[PDB]
Image (cartoon, rainbow, N blue to C red):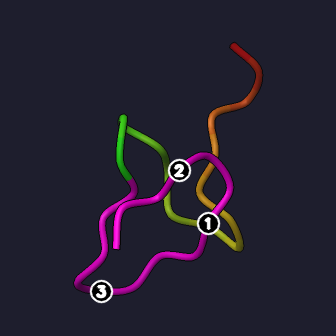
Amino acid sequence: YCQKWMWTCDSERKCCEGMVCRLWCKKKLW
């Protein structure tokens, strides 16, 4: 699954758009 803004990451799942894996992968603001 691709992470659209704050979503969950896995060892497989890498958070799209260059978001860091944490509780929620998200970009911090625009």
Q: Nearer the viewer, mark 3 or mark 2?
A: 2
Where is residue 22, by image quadrant?
A: bottom right
The residue under the point 36% across, 35% down is 17
Q: Which residue is mark 1?
A: 7
Q: Is residue 17 above or below residue 6?
A: above
Does the magenta stretch mainly form a helix, a strand or a loop? loop
| Stretch of the chain drawn in magenta | 1-15
Image coordinates for residue 18, horizontal then vertical, percent: 36, 37
**Local SS, label 1:** loop
Is mark 1 in CB contact (under 8 Å) with mark 2? yes
Q: Residue at x 30, y 64 (%)?
A: 14
Secondary structure at badge 2 equals loop
Looking at the image, is 10 positioned above or below residue 13?
Answer: below
Q: Which residue is label 2 attached to? A: 4
Mark 1 vs mark 3: give the one in front. 1
Precedes in sequence: disc 3 or disc 2: 2
Amino acid on which disc 3 is placed: Ser
| Label 1: how many Cα within 10 Å (few below 14, some 14–19, many 20+) | some
